[PDB]
Image (spheres, rainbow, N blue to C red):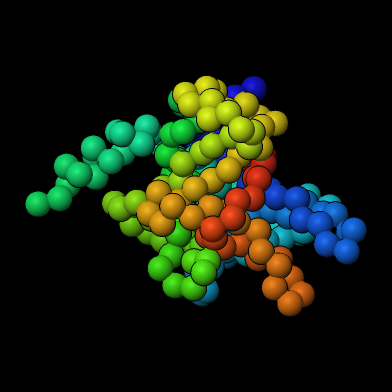
Length: 174
């Protein structure tokens, strides 16, 4: 099966510390604090706030042409920029300006690069233009900041940010 625009998906990462491995899913609440956070699975405790829709998939050239022009169920392909709408809130996953790693959260406005993420394979091949398959692990890079959607450990919990190092995400329909 291939990932496609309009698919409802969850984004999961694998977190290991002190030899305890677990799978975590990206989540956000509809209101209040806009920042995303991560839930442990095993099914997360609250699946309705982890669901995103792949709303658009455009080539980087197309997207940058679109945006430049404002200044005065398609298969996802590697290298394309995607827009991910959080189902529960209707807002979009976004690299924020606030804090070496930036915060990742939700916003309403998609006219700008902060809500766009380019998809890249996990391997040493760029595989540019190849179809993304369910089962592939992906690297997601912010079009605004060029940082990676990234798993971080704090003092006691796992967090998600946009950082200078990569994380592999599993994106599957659910």
